[PDB]
Structures are given as structure tokens and as C-alpha cells.
Amino acid sequence: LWDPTLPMIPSANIPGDPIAVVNQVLGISATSAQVTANMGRKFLEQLGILQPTDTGITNAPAGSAQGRIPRVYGRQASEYVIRRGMSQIGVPYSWGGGNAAGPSKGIDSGAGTVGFDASGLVLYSFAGVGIKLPHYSGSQYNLGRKIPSSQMRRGDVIFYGPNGSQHVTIYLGNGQMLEAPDVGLKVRVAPVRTAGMTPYVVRYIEY
Image (cartoon, rainbow, N blue to C red):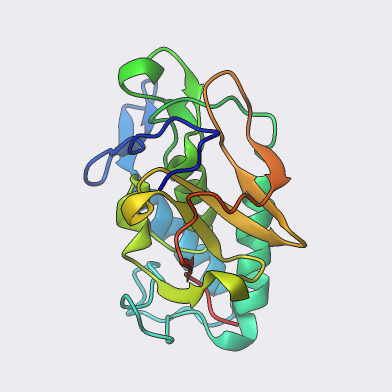
């Protein structure tokens, strides 16, 4: 039922729209959704397609094959997401860690450690193009569009455990995935594991 290489428990479940940026000097703070909207608007502006109605949030309604980002720009969007995640290789794992702005202090166990957990890394990566994801893998599994796992494609998101609750990674193609794996390790590229994998992956960006 679970990937037996990792703890056989649900991943950290961080509610709502957490504060992502705190600047004590300037006296400001902002949430993950704020940062994500701002990045989404910048991305749309860089494609030449920003509209006054755009908040910057680009998610498709769950199950729809139509999101805000045009299909002709989806490969570019996906590659930007992957670049963002890959830039984090070497950052420590932290249980509960990460927000749309970068690694962060975790929760519970991970309260004294700045880093990413699996769903935190995924949310950070996708935030660069305005795709807003909750900080819990099981909730991430309910968004986006399902693709059969046998047909996973670079940029799709792989899940593990019941309800996708254990672990989540970004598929890179060629049998490799980007993940924040477990305590004492760092964000890494690793071979895809099939044990405990859900029968679908999730696609957030169409192309």
C-alpha cells in the first residue's frame, strides 16, 4: 500500500494559505498564494498574454484539460517548474518544510530545520507559473488532471500511498523523478519507484 523505503504514514498536512515571506526589517509578510499570484502574473507577462482579469493563479478546474496557460506555452511553463525544482537539489529535507517562496521551517519534528518536504518542494516548483497547490500530498492528488501512471510524462506529478497521502515527486522523464525524500537527506533526483505508487499521476500543465 505504501512505498516501504519511506515512513508508512501520511505526509505533513499544513492547512490553508501559510505565510511564506516575513521581512522584519520592512515590516511585511505575505502568504504562499500571494507569492504564487505575483509569480503567475510575471510568467503570463513574459509570455505576452497578461490580462486585467488575471489574478496570476493558473490552475485548471480539477479534471479539466483547459487551464489558463495556453497549450503552446505549456512546455515552457513545465520546464520552468522543473528548473525551479532542480535548482533546489541539495537543500535539506524538513518534515512540513517549504512554501511558495522557498524552503522553510517545518512542523512537528521538522520545526528546527529549514528545508522542503515532498509536497512542499512540489508546491514551490509549480508556484513559479502560478499553479497554486496545497501543502499536503493527499490534497494535491485531488487537483489537476489524472493521467494513467503507465503514461506518465516529464512534468507530471507522481504520488504514493492511499489517497496519494505518503509522498509526491515530479517526474523528469527517462525513469527519474525529483523529490524531497526523508529526514537526513536532501532534495535529489532518484529512479522512479513503483511500490506504493498511485495508479494515476497528476498533470497540472497541459502541452
